[PDB]
Image 1 (tube, rainbow over the protein chains, first blue to last red):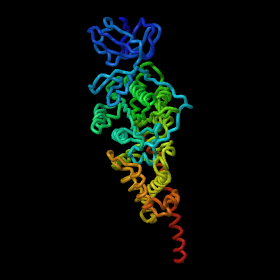
Image 2 (cartoon, chains in turn green, blue):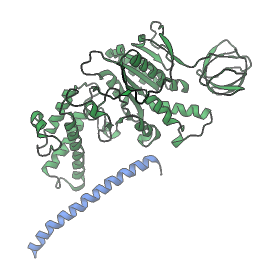
Image 3 (cartoon, chains in turn blue, green):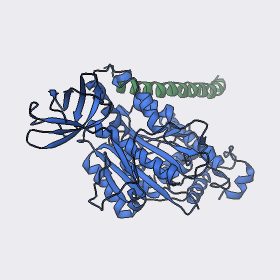
Image 4 (spheres, rainbow over the protein chains, first blue to last red):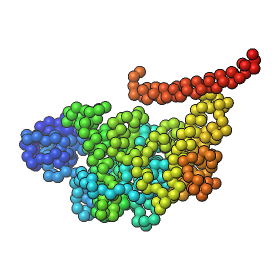
Amino acid sequence: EYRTIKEVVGPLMAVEKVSGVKYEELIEVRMQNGEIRRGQVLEVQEDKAMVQIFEGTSGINLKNSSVRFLGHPLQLGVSEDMIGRVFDGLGRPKDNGPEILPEKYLDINGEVINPIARDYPDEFIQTGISAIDHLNTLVRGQKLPVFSGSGLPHKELAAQIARQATVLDSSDDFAVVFAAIGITFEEAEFFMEDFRQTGAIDRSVMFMNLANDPAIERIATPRMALTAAEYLAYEKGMHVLVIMTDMTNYAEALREISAARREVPGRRGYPGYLYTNLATLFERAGRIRGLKGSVTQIPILTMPEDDKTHPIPDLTGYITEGQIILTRELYKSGIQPPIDVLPSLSRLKDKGTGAGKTREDHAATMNQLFAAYAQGKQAKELAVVLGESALSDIDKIYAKFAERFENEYVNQGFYTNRTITETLDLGWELLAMLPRTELKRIKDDLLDKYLP
Amino acid sequence: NPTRMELTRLKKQLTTATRGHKLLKDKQDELMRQFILLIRKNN
């Protein structure tokens, strides 16, 4: 134990006479009034170590307070009993439930998967959301993020996906790890209450970190959640869906720590190592050869000023296999969920679709719906520019198609769970508006089988 | 004035303006051809 506090600058403190102290090591501060606060080493030299106190430094007298180094960093106590439980960012119980006796304690950084040990995503995941399942299909082992924005309903979409996501057949279902990073209590309570009211909590492990929690707890949260996921998946053989919001809050926490170490920012004010950081998190996912279990990731982030060139969504897209984009234009028009299919993409979609996986008319109808939607939007624009005089009869149909596509297909509601069959069938009912001559991307083989 | 929000918005106005220019140019051409038929009859 050390009575050697040298400096206190905000929530930071410098401690001298250190030895055997490691980066990210946990500390414990005994104040002059006996009060106990914990912290973490952010930087360490021969003579001293810099620490940040979770609870802050208000009321601390340097001379009469003491510091103890715990000899270990933050660690997760893993067990299959985590299922059905709610924890905070540091893995501490939040639901006032029974005590958990850990199988073992794990470091939360994980290990990098050998690129040749990974198996390719194979199994279709039915989210119950048409604009995803059909046009931007999620496959087991993929990382497919939602790019949103302030005031957009990624909260409701996250809850919906966690609620409805399932694999056809299998019998064994999805264990869902849900990480909330730097969110408001009101949003955290929405998630927790939705999970309880639907019974989804029985399938889930939740790690809830709030906006007024320390920056170091926000940074720990995704790592705690992913450590839990890899344990359930790669050690217990479970299929795990990992949903994490808001990744932008995670990035802002990094900047705070980076500034405390006086590091010069990279592009747009973020650490130079932001890519490495995001890549280390998002690549903790996928199937592994010879293993039964898997990790599927859906990171969720808000794009600052709705800017896709911003470092956070820009670097994330380089790492993840596509992205689902929410837009203000669709939301203002009352489309729920407001998914814009044109810039949205799933890069592994061709791997989870077709006969045996979904249905044989999956790929063809997807390309056809996409083409007609873009063509219909062009037709609407034409009518505004040149008038209704310039529209042909085919043009007026495409315009009507795009209208119905947004309002009946994309706009399904945040509590509507569509089976892939229902989604594909609705696609055909919309394509039925068009003459058979217009359905070019569909072979007459499947056009004669499904077209109403 | 020169913010990233303005940039993205002006880039959008350019795409629209470019398309509108093409549509209007096609309209003028279509009107011109119909005019050619009528003006010969007028003559």
